[PDB]
Amino acid sequence: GPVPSRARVYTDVNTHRPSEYWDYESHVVEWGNQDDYQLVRKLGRGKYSEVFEAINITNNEKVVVKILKPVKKKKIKREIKILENLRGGPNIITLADIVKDPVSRTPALVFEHVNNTDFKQLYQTLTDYDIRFYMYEILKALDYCHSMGIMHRDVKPHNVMIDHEHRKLRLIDWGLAEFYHPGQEYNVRVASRYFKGPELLVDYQMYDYSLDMWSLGCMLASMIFRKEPFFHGHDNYDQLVRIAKVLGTEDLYDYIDKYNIELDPRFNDILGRHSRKRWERFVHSENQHLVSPEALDFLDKLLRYDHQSRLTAREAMEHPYFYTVVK
Amino acid sequence: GGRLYGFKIHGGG
Ligand SMILES: *Cn1cc(-c2cc(C(=O)O)cc(-c3cn(C*)nn3)c2)nn1
């Protein structure tokens, strides 16, 4: 079978915590008054959520309502529990209330308002200094949620909300988030295709927090090189081929060998043979102002097949890339 | 009935 693995850091946070903390199935939800909130305008839609800009009429404060769908139920408790556990953490979206429609029974989460600005929208104009600043702010959120025994599992530009005039950032959408229990074989059908780590792609189920660090490296690559997305696969299979064409097949097969991974037969004829392409090869006139030898060293330390070899969120925070961020 | 998912629609401060 595959070689076992444990997160290098924050391994036993859930192990030494009482079941009330991580046992979301047992969480009794405290429902608020739905009559306090009124819809202002449509903010977006997903495959299980409808997001709106709203107003609390009791104080006239702006809020964001996320109406949950019945497609994926009993997964509403995991999200609610994770938001309440992370409440107050640096750059973590604030769950302000939980409400339910008395007739349709459809639940809705009421969040603190943040400017409806995704990271994607800003990167096109961000300078080297703001890429470093916001990347550090994302790392504060990831170190916090990992320290609290939680993997986000959906790190992507869409899940980062920024109010640039206040240089204020929030990590949102905790709908795919999960509690880290060392030894757990998790479902690999998580994250978004372009941000899935090699572990998901080879069906290595005993992954951990380091999955989020791969997704973060994917975002950094996209930002410093102006290539959206950085790894553009046509499916989960081709996604690993796209990674292989950059990191190289040698290190992929060393990874599979190390963890005794049973590689799907489809990969034998599509993976092929590819040498490692140096990070500098992605540098050109339009993006050279966003690249530095520190940015490259840092990127190289995130985008690694072996989940155990990637920097932890706290180790990333200490990298020379962040020396220019003046606290 | 002009309520969306139980929420009334706001118009204007
Ligand atoms: C029952 N019901 C109410 C509404 C509705 C629709 C709109 C719209 O713009 O389409 C707007 C409003 C509204 C705006 N304000 C200030 N108060 N109500 C209400 N549709 N069906």
Image (cartoon, rainbow, N blue to C red):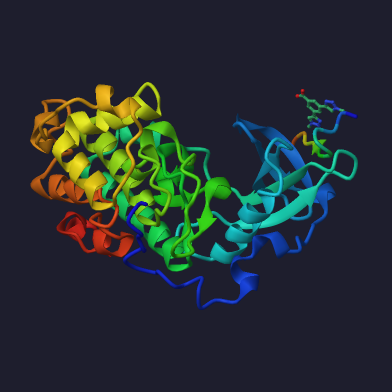
Q: Nearer the viewer, residue A113 or A85?
A: A85
| Image quarter of residue A68 | top right
Residue A9 lies, in percent from the top left, at 34, 68
Q: Nearer the viewer, residue A310 or A128?
A: A310
Q: Nearer the viewer, residue A232 or A240?
A: A240
At 71% from the left and 44% from the top, the residue drawn is A73
Q: How many marks?
A: 0
Going by the image, does A317 lie left or right of A300? right
Image-quarter location of ligand 1: top right
At 18% from the left and 54% from the top, the residue drawn is A321
Q: Is residue A69 above or below residue A36?
A: above
Camera sees residue A232: no
Going by the image, does A140 lie left or right of A172? left
Residue A222 lies, in percent from the top left, at 28, 34
Residue A289 lies, in percent from the top left, at 14, 36
Q: Quadrant of the C terminus of chain A?
A: bottom left
Camera sees residue A112: yes
Q: Nearer the viewer, residue A152 or A34?
A: A152
